[PDB]
Image: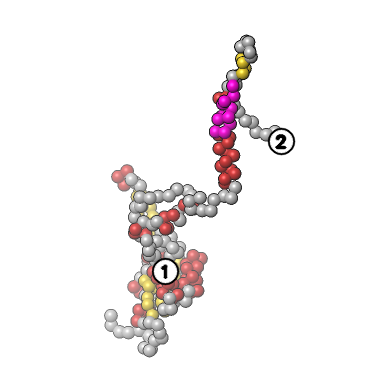
Amino acid sequence: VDYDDGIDFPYDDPPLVCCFGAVQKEFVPVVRVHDNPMHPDIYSQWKMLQWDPPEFGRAPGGPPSNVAISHVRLGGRAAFMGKVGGDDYGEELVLMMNKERVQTRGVKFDEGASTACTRVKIKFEDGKMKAETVKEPPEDSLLASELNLAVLKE
Amino acid sequence: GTSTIPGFNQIQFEGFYRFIDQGLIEELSKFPKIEDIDHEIEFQLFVETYQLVEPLI
């Protein structure tokens, strides 16, 4: 915007990449309707939909933390930018990213928030049950003042 | 056994259950309605009334 941050350095190799968003365990986002369901209870049949998948789920993606971990395992250097709560689950997620050698210096903690928890209120508009968000989870509550300008520079 | 390794005793388990369902009825039939030479006394079985009770031991 106006100036730079920190101290200029030649920077190490491989070049750093930044993954921005929420850090979650699994949680494939892409969901559509499939016409070939298996038994609702017997999950031992559900592997048959892994080798005959819905087309939208042939190579599913996930949260940016998955991309960061995969990039580091492939020999690259990655940093994750996001916010987690100050509870046990947030520390567990940050530990998972740390053991994978993903840079967590861009991770902001929120002591008053519950990681991966969203407050919603249930309403019955036009005869159908619905929900609306009361308090967003800390993964959706990263502020522009909480960014890490060194990571964004490198 | 479409998606998992089946039980190693499933063939014995399913065979015996088939015998209880259809083997008994199919064999309790063909039992002749026993009649004497004089035809006076006729003995017969009502196969639809067949039952098995759980073992006492």
Q: Position of residue B27 (x, y in %)?
A: 58, 29
User: In the rendered view, does B20 fall on the left or right side of A47?
Assistant: right
Q: Position of residue A58 (x, y in %)?
A: 37, 61
Q: Report which residue position mark 2 lands on.
A: B57
User: In the rendered view, does B49 fall on the left or right side of A89?
Assistant: right
Separation of marks 1 and 2 at Cα, in angstroms? 60 Å
Based on the displayed image, in which of its 4 quarters is residue A143 positioned? bottom left
- Give the letter of the chain under mark 1: A
Q: Do we see residue A133 in this rendering?
A: no
Looking at the rendered structure, the number of numbered marks drawn on it comes to: 2
Using the image as rendered, state which of residue A94 and residue A51 is in the foreground. A51
Q: In the image, which residues are magenta?
A: B22-32
**Amino acid beneath label 1:** Asn
Is label 1 in a helix, a strand or a loop? helix
- Give the letter of the chain under mark 2: B
User: In front of the other: label 1 or label 2?
Assistant: 2
Residue drawn at the location 28% of the way across and 80% of the way down: A1
Residue drawn at the location 38% of the way across and 50% of the way down: A36
Vertical relation: B24 (above or below) A89: above
- The outermost residue toward the left is A1
Whether residue A73 is in magenta: the answer is no
The circle drawn on residue A66 is 1
Q: Position of residue A3 (x, y in %)?
A: 30, 84
Q: Do we see residue A130 in this rendering?
A: yes
**Amino acid beneath label 2:** Ile
Based on the displayed image, in which of its 4 quarters is residue B42 positioned? top right
**Main secondary structure of the magenta stretch:** helix
Based on the displayed image, in which of its 4 quarters is residue A8 positioned? bottom left
